[PDB]
Image (cartoon, rainbow over all chains, first blue to last red; front, side, top):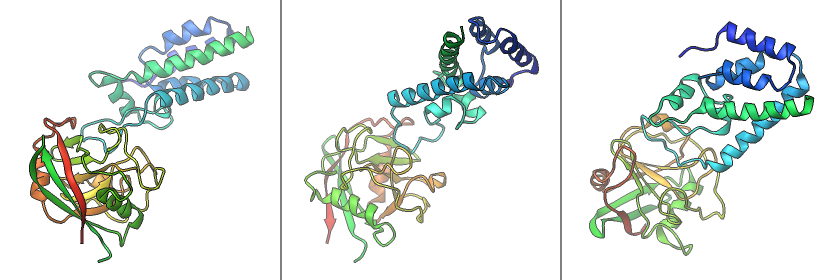
Length: 135
Length: 165
């Protein structure tokens, strides 16, 4: 496991700073974020300075997708069996209440729960919201 | 006595296995104790008689109490609603401890588990409310029907249950 690189990141920072929120941002975000864990995705978003209102639209989509994920994935009875991972909640997938190894476990269980791919999907939905507002 | 005693007569695919009794610590967690008590006598018109131990994990625990859906997604408290974690004063100190299963903080319903090992990491997430008095060897027998994921190999049911004295 490798936590994102200053370069793929300085790239994203420059994509967002020039191309604004033109549709091009979305394919780029998908490339720059291949195999990312939720924590990597959040560090890429957190690096984006300013564009406060757009960032709040993104957050609103993330919060809404996380709540839907919860709605459609009831919390299994605890206590969790030893050598088992609890199932991820929405907040876990968005990386606010999960750890990186936990993220990694999920991505690596057999079968896997692809938390990175799921959160990335929520992120892209929010990016589409931004793009349709600003362009 | 302040602390009631409850029995479960356990059967395996209808055949009698034996009886397990519990002391309930009403003197420490009276609201959690009383739910389990009342569910064990059937006095509310519903409860544990005929329900099963749907999840049994060897060297961990035996879980039951879902008498509404029989698979871990159901159960209900006598309180008309899931109830809060009363306290976490009592700890999971070894085999025989009786504690509440839940689905997060302050979601106690009817589901419970009997520990078959020390499970200290559960302290502060499950409310401990009783201990096996007699029949620990029956709980030990029950675990032989379990599996790493908890699926049981035969139907382990509470064929009868009630309050002693």
